Structures are given as structure tokens and as C-alpha cells.
Image (cartoon, rainbow, N blue to C red; front, side, top):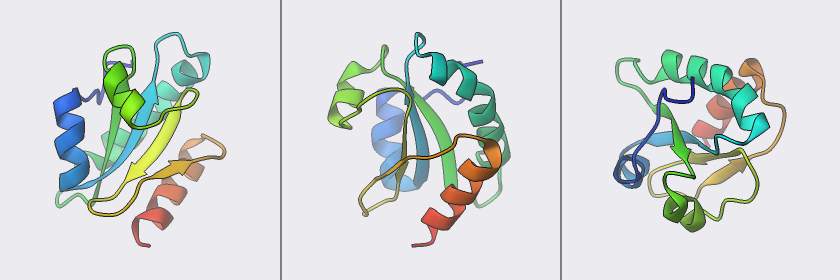
Length: 111
């Protein structure tokens, strides 16, 4: 369930410079991260396949890429960041249900 929408370090570095990304930094031992996996998969399934996609939904396993999580100043798990090419990243804080996540992502995209 956590295998879906996983990015490599290289995919992350280039992806966040090519298009908007809502990225989940997580750990397999993170209980909140586990419960969030199915919602994040739905978000990815809906948006990552869209034609002419303006946003992409991805994951970075911190236990696989500690160097990436360190560089992103990750504090606590999961950490939800929206990256926009050129602009500065925004850490999401708030309820983690599908409707709220989607609405915040959409509002934050056009700012």
C-alpha cells in the first residue's frame, strides 16, 4: 500500500523543478503514515494520470532516502509539503482526510 507513488531521490529532485508536487515524506514505522497511505493513494490515482496535469502526488520513504528528508528539513511524520517550481515549498498542517487535502492542494496551487 505504501509502494504506490514512491519516488526515488533522483525523481524527487527533478520532479519538484518540473511540476507542482504534493509530497508525503514518511516512514514505514510511522503509525499516522500507515493510516494515511490509502488516502494518499487515492489522491495520486486521481491526479497523477490526468492529461496535462498541473500537480503530481508522490511519496518519499525517509528510511530509503534519509539524505532527502534531511535536506527538506523534515520534522515528524508524516510531513506533507507542496512544491512549486521556482517558488518556495509549503508544509501542510491540518486534517488529513481526502476532501480537506484535495481542497487545500487546489487552493494552494493557484497562489
